[PDB]
Image (tube, rainbow, N blue to C red):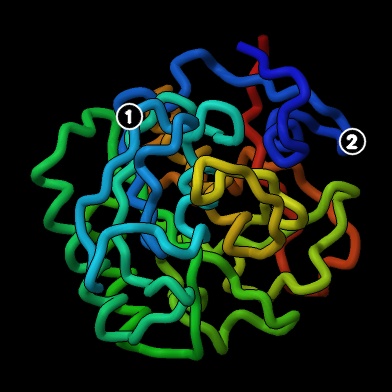
């Protein structure tokens, strides 16, 4: 399949070269996979989700995305127009309040919830979790991601937006999950994108156009918006049977576009998410 005038980030993960505008992808589009978006929630009524999005857990007075961040990332995972896996199921876990903040205990509880709730769902092609959130280092937030990953969920986490080594950030620094950094439309590391040895892969993260609350669209920048690109790709590749949850991060790393990024610090991997789709 092909999406003309796709968001540049979509076009980038189907292209070896920057600056293209068409998103090429297998038509299976992540059907049969599930991606938990652990965030502010999802405006599941957004027409761009076509009923493929639903809230399954909130840790606040409402399950509504009164922020837009979670709807934005869910859009990059599986929205019709702005999404990588346009057929995947999206489940919303609202661990961030409508101001984008959230305590560690509640983010651990949401990760612990996904690891169980997945056994309640139909995801024959496997389960992915996109975590477009972060904070200071925590062994207990790290271990929760490791538990979610070990339970059989592909865990993609943002590296953080601190222009620093991600090893001081959580869940970013947890070794076993897929720590995702942000690139930009000219194949540079995003000015804010964290780096370091713990990073496994880079994704489009600067000026990402996706869904927003109120049925609108918005472009925002952040490693939080690169994560859903890799989550979506993970669901995509898992639906294709190319990988599994346990090895999806390694596979995306092996099949990435190597060495395409500028201002990648020494010791940080130079790998850009890439579906390697051949029409």
Mark 1 and mark 2 in contact? Answer it, CB < 8 Å. no
Q: Is residue 154 visible?
A: no
Mark number, residue 19:
2
- Is 142 drawn above or below residue 10 in the view shown? below
Density class for disc 1 (Cα within 10 Å; few <14, some 14-19, many ≥20) is few
Query: The N terminus appears in which quarter of the rendering?
Result: top right
x%, y% of residue 196?
68, 76
Q: Quadrant of the C terminus?
A: top right
Residue 107: % across, % down: 31, 76
Disc 1 secondary structure class: loop
Residue name at image x 47 percent, y 81 percent: 170
Quarter-wise, where is residue 270 in the image? bottom right
Q: Which residue is mark 1?
A: 51
Residue 163's place in the image compared with 69, above or below, is: below
Q: Secondary structure at mark 2?
A: loop
The percent position of residue 195, horizontal first and vertical second, equals 70, 73
Most foreground residue, 91 or 154? 91
Callout 2 environment at 10 Å: few (<14), some (14 to 19), or many (20+)? few
- The residue depicted at 74 percent of the width and 18 percent of the height is 4
């Amino acid at each position: 399949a092909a999406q003309t005038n796709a968001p540049w980030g979509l076009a980038r993960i189907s292209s070896t070269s920057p600056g293209t505008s068409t998103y090429y992808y297998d038509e299976s589009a992540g059907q049969g996979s599930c991606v938990y978006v652990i965030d502010t929630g999802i405006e599941a009524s957004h027409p761009e989700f076509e009923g493929r999005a639903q809230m399954v857990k909130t840790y606040y007075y409402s399950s509504r995305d009164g922020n837009g961040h979670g709807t934005h990332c869910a859009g990059t995972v599986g929205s019709r127009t702005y999404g990588v896996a346009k057929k995947t199921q999206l489940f919303g876990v609202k661990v961030l309040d409508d101001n984008g903040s959230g305590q560690y205990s509640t983010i651990i509880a949401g990760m612990d919830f996904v690891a169980s709730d997945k056994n309640n769902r139909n995801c024959p092609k496997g389960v992915v979790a996109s975590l477009s959130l972060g904070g200071g280092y925590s062994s207990s937030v790290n271990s929760a991601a490791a538990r979610l990953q070990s339970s059989g969920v592909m865990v993609a986490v943002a590296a953080g937006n601190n222009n620093a080594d991600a090893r001081n950030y959580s869940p970013a620094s947890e070794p076993s999950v897929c720590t995702v950094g942000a690139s930009d439309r000219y194949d540079r590391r995003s000015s804010f994108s964290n780096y370091g040895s713990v990073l496994d892969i880079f994704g489009p993260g600067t000026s990402i156009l996706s869904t927003w609350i109120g049925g609108s669209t918005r472009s925002i920048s952040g490693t939080s918006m690169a994560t859903p690109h890799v989550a979506g790709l993970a669901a995509y590749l898992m639906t294709l049977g190319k990988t599994t949850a346990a090895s999806a991060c390694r596979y995306i790393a092996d099949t990435a576009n190597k060495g395409d990024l500028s201002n990648i610090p020494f010791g940080t991997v130079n790998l850009l998410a890439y579906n390697n789709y051949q029409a």
